[PDB]
Image (tube, rainbow over all chains, first blue to last red; front, top):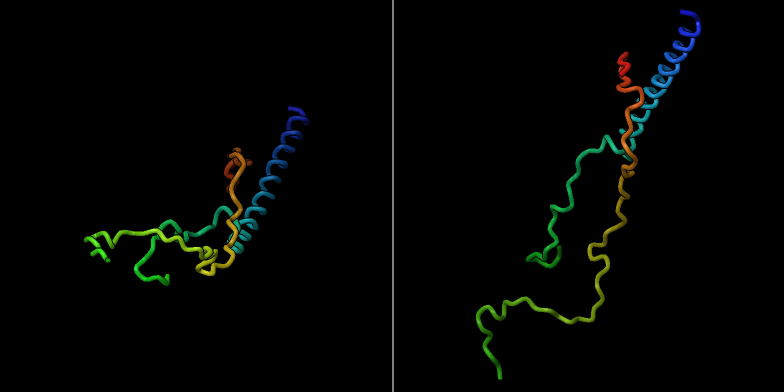
Length: 63
Length: 57
């Protein structure tokens, strides 16, 4: 095959691999930022739910 | 001029028409932390698939 085959095809290899390369670098730093600050969808750890608590009046007043 | 309260009658829960204002913050609670950034958008295919090592898909 001529050179337009391998040329445009190798372009496709490089562009796909470059976007994959930069997405990886973003993911490493995004994962770091999420684990450090915690303001993210993932890396969130379980906390006790409020609905378990009871608001009904108790025996003692001061509660 | 009194009446002996019947059994169970005095234990009835009752309503009191007090004019005291409601305690807005009885527990003296502070401001609460804002929720995490919520999730939105639609799920699109992962760009370049797995993107793990040499796996092209």
